[PDB]
Image (cartoon, rainbow, N blue to C red; front, side, top):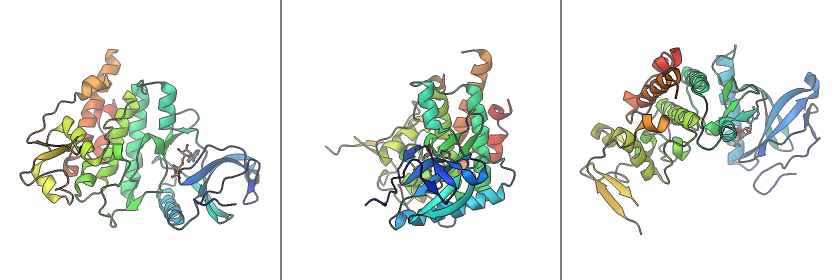
Length: 328
Ligand SMILES: Nc1ncnc2c1ncn2[C@@H]1O[C@H](COP(=O)(O)OP(=O)(O)O)[C@@H](O)[C@H]1O
């Protein structure tokens, strides 16, 4: 019934918890099997069942995902802060099963349907940003850090008008804040994580900014191969990291020398850079009608405030929701 890795495999037509009739597959995994089911106890209504991987460490993250989703759902009774709705939970053949609201597809899937480097319409990006900032508001209202905000973890409804922040498997409490430079998916990873500086809700704000650029351009903002390449790409837009920020970090020596100069790795190869000049043109890469062009400039102004290297100088959730791009 259970694989060596810890996967359940699943059978089409199988009834889970004597009510959930599995008909669809969606995708398995990675780290859990998400199946499409019909709840026979609730007039054959559509539901998504996340079957958590077995082993030891995966079940620990599953219960952690269960408690965090329960906290966010209770804090938002009217469902206005765009977070995934957990219906209930059950156990099936050793695996923990999470019953979720039915959603059409993730933002990575919609982007592929839009085309190669096409991106979503500015009106859709505007609506999506507001909902993403509302998700950050609830995340900050509670003491939770998503720590994996990317198009793959943002699900959309059938009409694609409403989005939901999903996958709380890598989520953590603010008081915990573990010293690790591999926190958050590499491309959406904040500079304070890499340097080893104290991090908070700002990492989720940075990730949102990375997604917003990708939502409009259809391209990854910083497609860095390593943690050192991620810093170089981040500095190619904002210039060299401030001296006060580098000193606060833990992994300073891995990227910066004693003279506070960046060491770019390109067979090892190390090139020392004294001052990094802002070469990346955010406006040129983002861009035709004047009503749409004005909205693009507003997105550019919002992105410059989100992409601030120092998290203390980063735009707040309230100011991002009140921004000219959202308010029109
Ligand atoms: N509530 C849902 N409704 C419909 N599909 C979902 C839902 N939740 C997740 N999925 C699908 O399953 C995919 C992976 O789910 P996820 O939470 O990331 O599992 P894991 O953390 O093991 O990778 C999502 O990208 C989405 O396609």
